[PDB]
Length: 328
Ligand SMILES: COc1ccc(/C=C2\S/C(=N\c3cccc(F)c3)NC2=O)cc1O
Image (cartoon, rainbow, N blue to C red; front, side):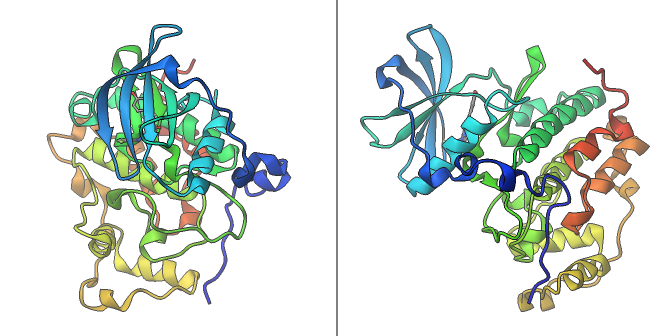
């Protein structure tokens, strides 16, 4: 069978936490007052929820209300428990309340509000310095949640809220996040297609926090190279082919051979043979102001097939790419 794997950091965090910390199925929700919140406008809809701007009438402050569609109560408790565990951490969205919506007959999560700019327009305006600054702020959030025993599993631009006026960043949408337990096998149907790590694309279930670092590398590559998304697959099979055309097929085979994994035979006629490319080939006159040797080295150390070889969040924060970022 497949070779097992463990996280190289924060491996035992949940082992030595009290069971109440990670045993989300036993969590007892503390419900707030549903009439404290007045919905103002709908902001979005997903497969699992709708999100609204709202006003908390007990303080006349804007909040954001996520009304869940019906889903396994286990998954609802998981997201609530994770949000409560991480509340107050650096750049983690703050869950302010949980209420029962009388119309949907489901829980409604109430969050702090972020006056954000959509990434489609924000990414066209960010400077080299802005990108380093906000990448550092995302790493603070990821090192925190990893240090707290949690993997996010849906890192992508749409889940990073940025109020550019106040240089404020929040990592949102913890609905796919999970507790890391050594040796646990996880669902590989997580993350958005363009941000799925090779471990998900080869169906390796014993993955860990390092999945988030692949997704972050995909974000970085799209920003410094001005190509969004960077790995633009048309389905989950073509997604791995897009990656292999950059990282090469020999190291893909080294990866699956190390964990004694077999590729889906449907790759026999689509994968081809590809050399590993140098990142300089993606540099051109319209993105070179966002590229430096430090940026390419940092990106190279995030985008590794082997989840065990990627920078950890803490290691990433030590990288020379962040030397120019003003520290507080
Ligand atoms: C503008 O300010 C904020 C915006 C969002 C959030 C928190 C969210 S949105 C979410 N899921 C979605 C995403 C898209 C569509 C959908 F129907 C649900 N999960 C969270 O935690 C907090 C804010 O302050």
